Image (cartoon, rainbow, N blue to C red):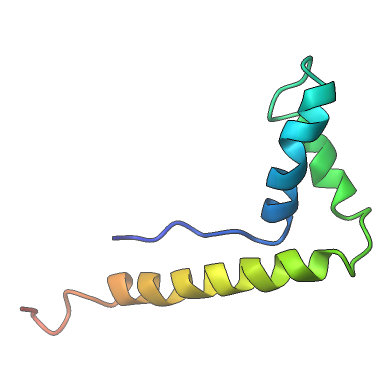
Length: 79
């Protein structure tokens, strides 16, 4: 039911590094170690984003369809 906006590119990268920086930063939270990612992502090589993006896209795409399929439903009336 009502899908939940999958990855957006950054999302991947985030995951990949969070536990690593945090590994060195057991003084941060998934709000600050994450904050860092938030920035680094823009500061990556926009060549290295490409992979994450293709994934994020595929994922949100799925959503947009199943969401549109769960948003534009209960209209035929509807069995």
